[PDB]
Image 1 (cartoon, rainbow, N blue to C red):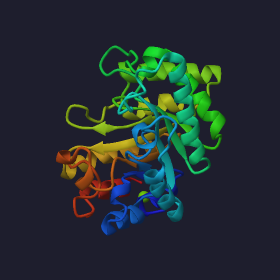
Image 2: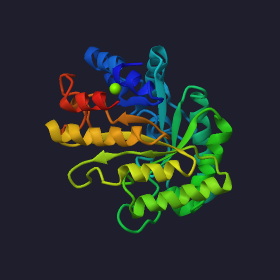
Image 3: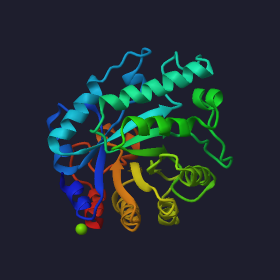
Image 4: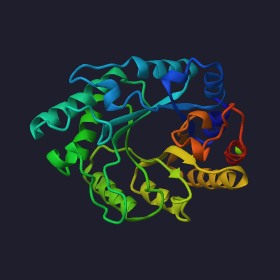
Length: 302
Ligand SMILES: [Mg+2]
């Protein structure tokens, strides 16, 4: 579906966008989405606090609006995200280990159940590693109380619920080979060696002046692909403007299309207007939904 989505599909990939339910009724937002993209990711609507703010009480309406729209347009859906340290409801962190484990598996199971057979890929675990040089696990209720094994447990639970979804580990600042991506690499290699059910590694790819597109972006994607997983660019945006921004997008698209198991790219929003990094004007469409030089470069590269 869509101009970018169909261009990508011709070479066996998808092209998606992060979507917000609260903008779906806006004519130009919906028109741009439907004209351009072949996959969607709910920006906020499937996060823990959005779907289970009260324990064992699930609120799917907002995410259902995005999924229903996608299905009506023949678009793929990425589920985002099941287990994540960030933006948890207040009551998750005080739970003792045994009850946290139960609550985590219950959350995975009921969320995946509601969307069974409708989800192309799940971000099962998100952002489990620290930034910087340590390669260490990030502190979280899951890491602190369940230990290193919580990631494997989450993937095992996920696999029992919906065998048809690709199960992804997702993270940022993992674009080049560095201490952080090395820690993820070690984990995924170990998972694949032992037959842990992981199908994919997501690379958020939030690029800016301090975190530029690295010279080894392609080689890094390739080494992950070579472990026997798909790689997905999940949250792509690139701060800047004009030819410099366009050339950065070319670099990224070229790298994905050069890696046979890079199965798709999702940009983190439809329009600059609603970007989480709006002052960096980092997307393919401006505030009036007009195609930017960045868009032209992406389309020409596909
Ligand atoms: Mg072409």
